[PDB]
Image (cartoon, rainbow, N blue to C red):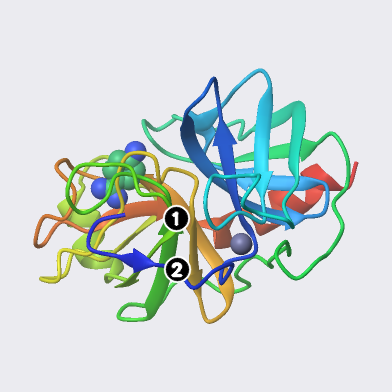
Amino acid sequence: IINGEDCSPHSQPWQAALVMENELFCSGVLVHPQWVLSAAHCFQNSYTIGLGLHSLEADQEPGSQMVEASLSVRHPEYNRPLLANDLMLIKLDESVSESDTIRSISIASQCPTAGNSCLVSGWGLLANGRMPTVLQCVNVSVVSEEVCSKLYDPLYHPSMFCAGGGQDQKDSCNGDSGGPLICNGYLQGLVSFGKAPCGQVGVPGVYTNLCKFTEWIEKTVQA
Ligand SMILES: NC(=[NH2+])c1ccc(N)cc1
Ligand SMILES: [Zn+2]
């Protein structure tokens, strides 16, 4: 997250983290007590999801569950077109509790609207160059489908939407992938990609257009 701040301790209780060896590579979103939503390019044969964590310290977090899983469904249309349909559903090895630091969120019912101020959180690279210690928070608004489609032509696809790109250089970055983008208390999208370096004036970051997969996500979970 570039030019963000420290989220209020557990202000985003749906936020999830994907960890490999000793590091952290992606984030996710708890959209169901047994299902985590993330970005397809974060695929892994097996996962280790950290929930209810303001900091990546399971010890400093009394209320946090480091669950695991292995079943993950990538969208059939991922990367076709290139970078398109970037979303994936990870099924937890076990349900989770419904606590005050771990809560599932609902997926945006309607689609993005330009200028609509939203919020994105994650543990990716900071405004400077490093890894943060606690979840970062930054606010970015949605860009008209016109500006977005033109700015990223031909990579732009209906399964994506831009946000940010303002002169406040607020944007996402490596490590924030899969992170959640909330608008009006709803999960509008997920961190997908964007031109590097991050935080370029006029170059908003692209996210997954979840409103265009509401039917698929449901269908996939109920089977
Ligand atoms: N928002 C961005 N510029 C971005 C998002 C994801 C990513 N992997 C790299 C850059
Ligand atoms: Zn805490």
Q: What residue appears at the point 44 percent right and 29 percent down from the top-left corner?
A: 79
Inspect the image, locate mark 2, and give the three-letter code of the amino acid beneath it: Cys
- Residue 123 position within the rendered picture, expressed as x and y whole percent measured from the top left: 42, 48
**Residue 150, numbered circle:** none
Q: Secondary structure at mark 1?
A: loop
Q: Mark 2: is the Cβ under 8 angstroms from ligand 2? A: no
In this view of the protein, which residue sits in the foreground, 34 or 158? 34
- Residue 128 position within the rendered picture, expressed as x and y whole percent measured from the top left: 17, 49
Snapshot quadrant of residue 62:
bottom right
Q: Is residue 42 above or below residue 99?
A: above
Q: What residue appears at the point 71 percent right and 49 percent down from the top-left corner?
A: 217
Sort mark 2 into few (<14), some (14-19) or many (20+) by Cα contacts within 10 Å: some
Q: What residue appears at the point 41 percent right and 49 percent down from the top-left corner?
A: 133
Q: Is residue 137 above or below residue 215?
A: below
Asked whether residue 90 appears in the rendered view, the answer is: yes
Inspect the image, locate mark 1, and give the three-letter code of the amino acid beneath it: Val
Whole-angstrom CA distance, mark 2 to mark 1, is 8 Å
Do the CB atoms of the residues marked 2 and 1 lie less than 8 Å apart?
Answer: yes
- Residue 159 position within the rendered picture, expressed as x and y whole percent measured from the top left: 46, 50
Q: Which residue is mark 1?
A: 134
Q: Which residue is mark 2?
A: 7
Quarter in which the N terminus is drawn: bottom left
Q: What residue appears at the point 41 percent right and 74 percent down from the top-left corner?
A: 118
User: Left of 222 or right of it: where is 150?
Assistant: left
User: Left of 221 or right of it: where is 197?
Assistant: left
Snapshot quadrant of residue 202:
bottom left
Which of the marked residues, 2 or 1, is nearer the chain's N terminus? 2
- Residue 81 position within the rendered picture, expressed as x and y whole percent measured from the top left: 40, 33
In this view of the protein, which residue sits in the foreground, 51 or 92? 51
